Image 1 (cartoon, rainbow, N blue to C red):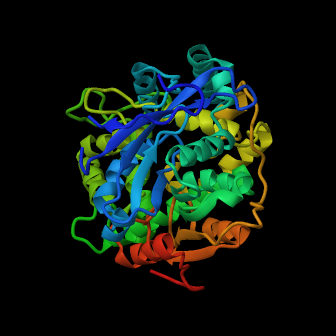
Image 2: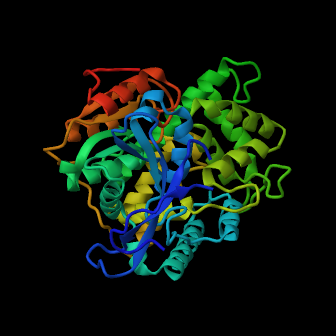
Length: 472
């Protein structure tokens, strides 16, 4: 519906708090082919209540996460001063959620069937099974999307979309807040449109120069550290289902989740009983645990989920895994999972070397024993991107944007998903400021911490950056 060239966004009330307005923006699928296929990006806008500086455009990360949904969430925790001075704007990146066309690969049944599998058998036969499933997944993506849209969903094109959004909002310069993956949008935008950046907050950092395997292993270490902090906390509390000795927590954890796999056939699930018909598979138990380690706000749920497992029940861990997968109460998945893969697979060269992948699994098992089953087998499956039918549109490199205004990178000391040091490195590459938050969670801005939010508010409004060494 949105007209292919700079037709202004037609705003209409969303059908929802704060007089929110909604509209669509047309962008070209291929920027080298502006008369070609068009994508329609969905936008949400919460008008400022005071003297408007401009729009605060956010991205929640993922990739594959809806910026409209995140804006609705952020609206509730937005500081009064930011609400006064900025229109809060969310957008769904190309291919995500309400934007069109939307990346779709799996049916709801495809996803359910995969989650029912233990996903633990890394024998040659098990690796072949996983890689066959992966090839069929990629075939489904190609069949539903076509190679042309898949080729162009990457962050390099999201950054160009973002400048079109800036201009469509009437802003001369971009004020931007990005979480996790959204800091790759931020630094890509910073490199291509440095003269358009008014202000940037980047919470939970992606280092675009990282080696993909070492970044994955650092992420594995981040989740093991988070697991360790969760379990040492749990050990102080009565009835801790992992026990009172945190040196034994990984062992006790495996005594609870390992029985969900048939000990004589690793392909056979023995799911824990739930009220849901699915029951709790081993793979969903791990995924639900990973979900809970995103925030101490979810640690009570992990404790509930593990206490249930003592009695061979799995309802809370299943619900946590559903939250991770974004499967709603009617069994419908949103498209975040499929979009996340399709975007990740074009944002850098995939790992295709079998030895590197096998060595990565050998190391991951030692770095993060909570989420590995049994023993190293000598084999491991290639990731989905090794089979991707469309080439990368970005290459790892250190951010180089010399004219860029000072920016703020927020980094949490025991962030499991984007570890602390990645924020230090990103702030170094941007020559920006590093704001430290001491905690065991992924992201922190506009999530209840006045110390963080006061720094962010002063930067968004006055351009003031935190002093060197600032901590919250």
